[PDB]
Image 1: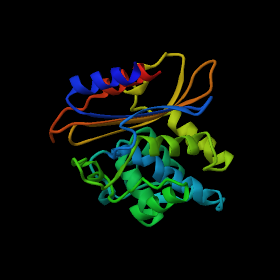
Image 2 (image 1 turned 60 degrees about the horizontal axis):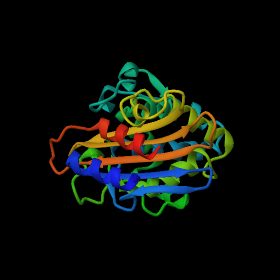
Image 3 (image 1 turned 90 degrees about the vertical axis):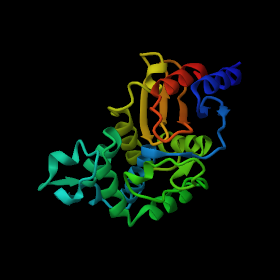
Image 4 (image 1 turned 135 degrees about the vertical axis):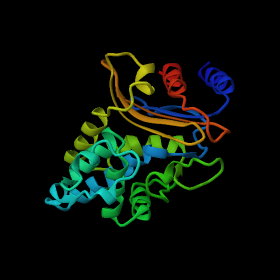
Amino acid sequence: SVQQQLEALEKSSGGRLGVALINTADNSQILYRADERFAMCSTSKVMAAAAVLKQSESDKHLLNQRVEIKKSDLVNYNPIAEKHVNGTMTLAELGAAALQYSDNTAMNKLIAHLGGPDKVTAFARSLGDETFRLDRTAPTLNTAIPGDPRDTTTPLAMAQTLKNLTLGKALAETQRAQLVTWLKGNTTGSASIRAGLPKSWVVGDKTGSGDYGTTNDIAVIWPENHAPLVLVTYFTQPEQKAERRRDILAAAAKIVT
């Protein structure tokens, strides 16, 4: 069965695997450690991007507002913000770079705009998400220490909230459509969930990775002749310097789909 398969995969991998698949045709689920907390790592960038889209519902000027990018702004991983030092980026460009390239300076500017990590958590609560918590900025939100509650959520909570954000009630249509366009344009997810799926299927995703070989990916999947599926695959290991295992997320996605 699927549960036995996921159990075997988890056992031979040497880590802890969390899976939540929601089939939106009937709202049936496939769950594996779906109520356990996992460090989100960069999959939390979706909630920061969505929090700014929610604001743009009430403020027409918002997404075009330009933000200066100083050399002092740069942290470790800034592939897009590094091309803009001494120049500017709009909040829409920051949203895009945070999601499609996992840029950490882009994430931090969006949190700075919102008023801090606690404002992202308050946006999550407003969505009915009682589990999500964002406590730090990038990149220390990637420490992924075993048993630390900071910057964590559960696979089921993130699968429900990602469904509501991309396919449901969370955002007004233009904002929901923009978030979906940014997720489908992701450039960092080829080796994760996408690699375990039929090539014809359209996928929007956000990967995350961190210490303790924490390897995450959250995805909305549009099969060619069926209703969408929402899949969250979180994976973490007992040792701090473990390698990431994107192939375990592709193996789990192959099993549940």
